[PDB]
Length: 300
Ligand SMILES: [Mg+2]
Ligand SMILES: [Mg+2]
Image 1 (cartoon, rainbow, N blue to C red):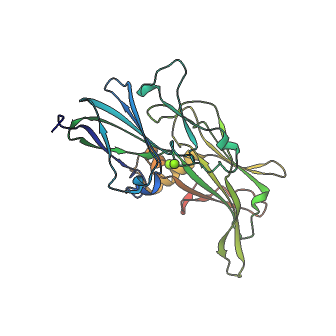
Image 2 (cartoon, helix red, strand yellow):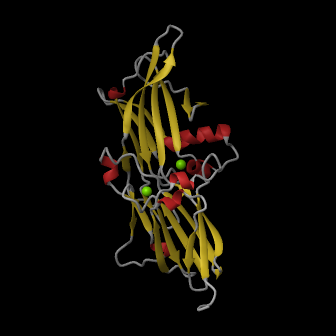
Image 3 (cartoon, rainbow, N blue to C red):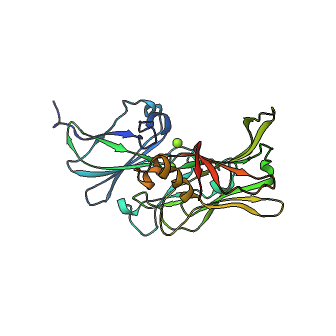
């Protein structure tokens, strides 16, 4: 032979932090950024994977490393050209584990062709190396969300989407190294898709036509420094018919169906949201019952 035994790690990347409690990494993460830090948190290396090998569930990242204990950080949706977020380093400050920040590219808030955000995934792992590579799994979570807002008349008469403006105000486009949100100033999300949809027919054979808006946002978190808002405004008179604390309303679904689940876990595991608001003939919101993810929730 020539050399001593190969040494390092062999990493598996999974995304099972969803409501199905099942790995969807192969079908959801198309680009991977893997960062290597030493035991003290100092930068060592970066590995970027954008190929078809990510669709293989048997995929492992073999890393030849000097004997030691390492901390690995994985990002999904940062590497390919479709990406909505950027790695951010503070000029003058280091490149270590605790110096990394990820921010949304501000052009995604306004460019209609970029409003529907590319999935952002994150996970980390501390793992010591071994002869013939130690095995470790980087368990990842999804940071982006899709919220479909529906306006439906209680009597079944149509709702014209063009009569309304839909917004989500939040302060959630800057992430620290530990994937927590950093206060960076309020942003306004507007719909990437808006129109009308069918909700079936009335007993009089009349089609029920609803208004919808799809909004794509960054991480939904319970925190004491920001209360994200969902706002629905009538264009003609500027009246805000809906103005609610979005996170509180979603957690009314958790309290009903997933009472033992952690609030943050629920906000992270679920990434596909839908909310139906019922309107009176004057197009005012009937503040009694709504639908969250097809489940009827009492507000008061
Ligand atoms: Mg990608
Ligand atoms: Mg989520």
